[PDB]
Structure formats: C-alpha cells, structure tokens
Image (tube, rainbow, N blue to C red):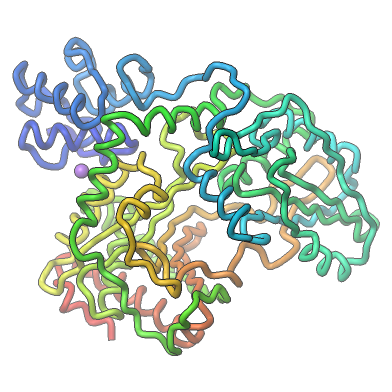
Length: 520
Ligand code: NA
C-alpha cells in the first residue's frame, strides 16, 4: 500500500471508485498503483470497460500501463479530448449559442416570473487614496473586452433563451460626488434590474465622498457571473488599473455552454442522472427542525445572521480528525452538521444542500460566468452508528456526488416531479458551506481598498438556514444565516454552541455512537 492521499479532483474520485469495485480493495487513493494493488491484465481491461460504461471515457490499455497510478491516469483524462465526452474545447463560431442550464432558469424566472433585483450581484468598496476616475473606467472597459460574459446579451431563438455575444459594447463609468451618508442610501437605490437584451450586464458608479475617499459601486446580473467570478473581476480590475498584462483565456463560457448541451445527449449524462434518480428514488425526507414561530404558508426571505468562533484548539483537533480518518475538514464538518440537524429534528435521514464551484477542470477556473452548482447531499445519521462510520458514509456519498456532479440541479428537480411546498425549497431546506477566509484589504499603489457597507447578503435568507464554516487564520468561525420568520437569535446562538459541543465530542472520541453524543 502506498501512503493514502484522498481524491483531489473529479477524475481522481471517479477512477478511485472504479478501482475499488474492480479490484475489491477499499480506500484507493491518489498515489495507489493498480498493479501494486494486485491488478493484472484481466482486471486492467475491466477498469477500461467500467470507465467506458459509466463515463464514456475510452482509456487505452497502453496508457493504464504507462500511467499506473490514480493521479497520473486522472491527469491523462484531464488533458485528453480524444474519446472523452467531458472535454470542453473551443467551439465553432455561430450566430447564437445555447444558454447553460443555470442561465436558462434565471432567464425564464427573470422574464416570466418577475424576479425584481433578486439576480443582482451588487458590491461596494471603500477606496481611500488618490484614485483616477478615468483609469477606473478604462480598467472596466478592458475587463469587458476580456470577458465574453460581460459582452453577452440574451434573446429567444427557436423558443429557447440563447446567448448573443457582442463584438464590442458601450460602457461608461457613472461618476457622482456625494456625502458619505448620501452614499449609504444611494448604494441601495442603485441596485436596479437589468434588461437582459442589452450588454454589458455590468454597471459601475464611482462616488466621491471626500478629498481622497471614494465608494465604488458595481452590479452585474447573475446570469453572466457568480461568487468566484466576482473575485476574479475584482483581482483583475486591480491588476488592470496598475497596467498589468493578464494571461490569455483558452476557454470561454459559451464553450462550456455548447459542451453542456452536447453532453446532455450522451450515455455519460444518463449515468450522471441515474445516480441522482437512484439516490432519491424512495421516500424523500422533509427536515423537521423545531421552529420558534409557525412556518409561514408562503416562503419568507427575511433573514439575520449570527457568528461564533470555534477556538484554536478545536479547529486544530478537527483538522487532525480529518487527517486521521482519511477525510477532508469539509467532510468532518458536514458530518457534524448532519448529527446536529438529526438531534434537533429527531430524524435519521437528512438532505443538506452543498454548493460547489462547478469549475471541475483547470480551464473553467479563470472564466467569468455562472458555474456554481448545488448538490443535494443525503445522509443517514442513525443513532446506532458510530460517528466514525457515519463520517465514512458522508465521505463516500460526497465522493459519489462529486463523481456525478455533471447533472444540473435544475434537471433533477424537474425529473423527480414534486413534493414541493411554497413554504420550503426543493430537496433541502438547509445549506452547508465551508470557505478559507479572504482579505479585508488587497491594496493599490496609491490607494487602500476595504468594505463600505456590512457586506454579503445576510438579511436575505433563501433557506430555513444556511450554515457557514469559515477558516479565519486564528480559528474556524461558525456562521448561521437564518429565516427571521422561524427562529429567534437566542435559538440560533444555542444551535451554534451545540454544533461546537458535537464537534468537541467527536474530536475527543470519533467512535462515539451518534445517540450517545451528549449535545444537551
Ligand atoms: Na466513491
């Protein structure tokens, strides 16, 4: 046995799963060698067959011999377009391009459902320093030229929303001089709907609030961006303002969108789908959290947030527990979150929404566009299970989920029919996320950048609650954004403390049985 390294990519996960089945060996990791694990020619051919059947990827036998470890063979698949239906390559020029599944839903909701400013992505930044307004504008103009998503409009062609990519588009920086307090009210009123027929779907206001003090207001439509894209846009704006040259983009959003449409007709897509249909084939559980107030008959989006630090000692213990069990910190926390919900809800079958970046290939990482996907993660925190074995179930289901991530959540919801309810969300009523901090000031040559308004969107709650773990450098912090119509601050602060008690207990003794975990 090689040292265990847990799968780090979608292809490492997919391959490892296949090797485990074919070889009948558990816990195959990135450094494991097929032939060291006991495979020979017969079972190598079975691995090739299995990857063809499950993923429509044709791996020559010669390559398995040449690249006998999970990490090498995964790298080969990532770098190979031939006989790989998952490969995203530059597409032939066309008058219009299909929208992605996520774009299609946003378009339809925006146009037929009347979704106001719900798909806006506003941000504000306090800039203290010299700052040249014309250079601000010029950097955005370059960004718009660079990123096709910022030159994309939408039209309906043959009954489908489609992407209309524009050569060049008009853009001007909106400049104003206001009081700081006036800026605070403006920043809210400046959030306004976008006409989806008109590129660019980004707008910028620069507000001079003093001498060397500015607020930069930026907004864009979620159909052409996401959280990761906003980070890219910010970083590249700062670089472009300094006059830096940015690296060329091999692949664009329309390439991904065309691929997704082609992929939808493949045997591989049917297998991606089949996993999810099987997973939710039986009785789909509805989370029964105790609420302080009666659940409204229509969904309420009013939200609030609370945050608490886990402490250095516990954060370190959780890291070591992940290390010790062959899991990620993400998995340990998700596992702990499932037991938290199980105890509050008095249930042993629970679905938690887990957002993923959707950027499962190197080429997708630098693209500005809508990639974020959600996986409905189902687990069964039964009282008799040890946390250790439950955590392994969470790991296994996570890896399986990541291996079948190329099925749009939009398709799953429609394909499963409905057990819907307007007072709650499809498949899951809570979301779990885990992040690694991010800088309060990244700075410019003559300026300093920082937040202006209280940041993020914690006042709006799409789900009953969203549980967020953030590794802040000196500790992991636990954030809960919750529906004001359902929970008091007191209840949610206690909910958070109970998570930390569960976390402490499982670090103390990972083999404790779920029912024996004294949460209080
Ligand atoms: Na697996």
